[PDB]
Length: 107
Length: 53
Length: 197
Image 1 (cartoon, rainbow over the protein chains, first blue to last red):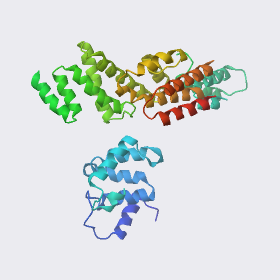
Image 2 (cartoon, each protein chain N blue to C red):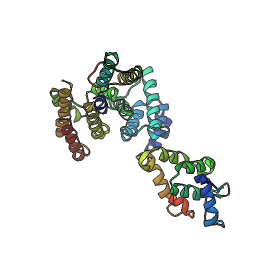
Image 3 (cartoon, each protein chain N blue to C red):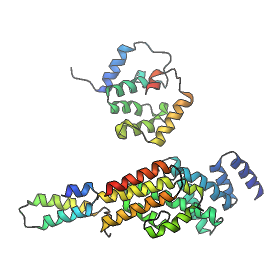
Image 4 (cartoon, rainbow over the protein chains, first blue to last red):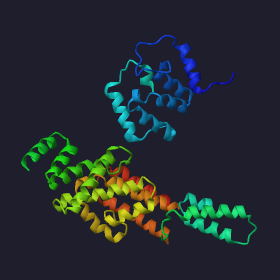
């Protein structure tokens, strides 16, 4: 039938492994799936582009995460700049150390 | 030789070798002479330390 | 003039330097504007100036204060003022260094006559460091390394003797100067000079 795009595959992967919505998810959905689940399993499959497409359709919801992620995809060795890397880590550590969305924590 | 120079940020010396080669009477095709010149042009357009603008 | 300093004074006491500068600058109190502007710049001198960063947002206000302070011929005492325009030059030195414009960045540091490059200047440059603002001595570590890494890159590209001589100069200067992270810095400086030979 043809290997579908990593995005549509992941979407057709979320259908199975989470049939019902978990009540602890955050930042809404994207085309019927939680935005953070798509980002994680896309990065897990190794297709950062497929993950960034997900981000582009949730620009308003994800807040400042867009400019941070777009830097991660650009910078080599899967590392951000110390300055920006510091900005996000402190934010996560500030009030998101224990968030009800595990996929958000992971990413 | 030019590859050695460039990795050592000696771009001007590489541009010199490439240019002379392009003007020479060695058996070099026109298209190769075009590549040599194009590289020299790039290498001479960037700073090389110890050499005047 | 008083209340603008009163309001500027408290906001200064509450670590709101970026505001206290705008307020003190509103009352044309350059003694305080440049003082605070020295504190906000020193931490960001070696940092990477990137769009919307805290460097751009501070550098661009400092330059908007440099023009308006030259076009209007305003200046604080030479201590506060000298350091303020000196940091602005260094901020340019790293903005050129982080961009790969090695030749251009080398020329700037040479003008400042802050780091000696010929053995003859070591005695006087070393004495000057003693009375330069600590907002400058703080960033001496990153300046020596960038300058060294600059000579370091230019070496891989007579001239060899000249770079080698300058390499030595930086080391002896750093050897006679007690400063921030002199341990890691003095070691790295010596290693980069060995690879040259």
